[PDB]
Image 1: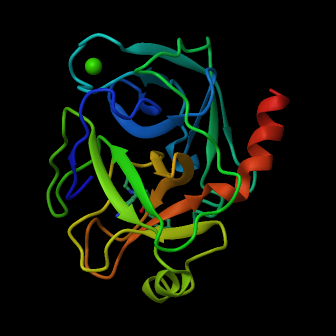
Image 2: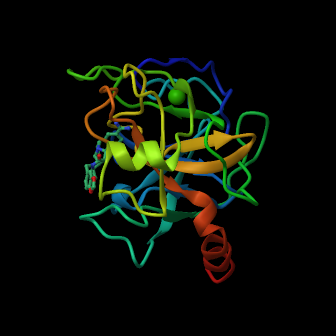
Image 3: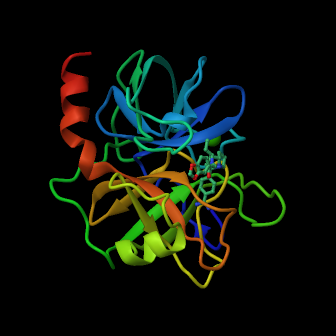
Length: 223
Ligand SMILES: CC[C@@H]1[C@@H]2[C@H](C(=O)N1Cc1ccc3c(c1)OCO3)[C@H](c1ccc(C(=N)N)cc1)N1CCC[C@@H]21
Ligand SMILES: [Ca+2]
């Protein structure tokens, strides 16, 4: 997260760290046995880490749970990043509490100007790599489709939206991928891609989760 603020420990209880010996992606807990992340975060050997603040220190409230399966959207396209979403099933159900909790799926898509909360443990600088220990937070609005498509002509599908600041200086970045964009208490986005981080006129692009709710529900029901 570039230009954000320290969330505070366990203030974002649905936030997850995907770990393979190191943090590589975020995710969101959507019930006690399933996580939503980005398709481009796919790998084998994923451990899900719940209840984290400092990812480098065991502080209490952590639960480490292996992924038993990862389900990349079958129409995910690695070139265009269309359908950049993946479901992860936990080996065992998480123990839900004040500090470990699920986030609701949306019943409707969010409109432009909706202010959202984006969080993660990714890079906090644009040019240069500085990773935080603790979870960072950023408040950012959803941009209009017209502004999104003028920023990234020809690259924006109906399954994507832009959020952030055209003036720059505030954005998600490397390591934030697959993390949550939560607006009015519902999961509306997944950190997917962008052009650098926090560059002027290059806002972040996010998977539009409201387009996948039935897929999510049908997939979880059958697995
Ligand atoms: C694996 C994808 C990679 C991903 C994300 C991204 O931007 N990519 C580049 C990419 C790939 C294909 C594309 C694309 C961008 O635009 C159209 O098609 C991602 C990324 C980069 C920048 C932001 C951001 N500024 N909000 C958000 C996510 N990077 C960081 C680490 C993983 C890598
Ligand atoms: Ca920790």
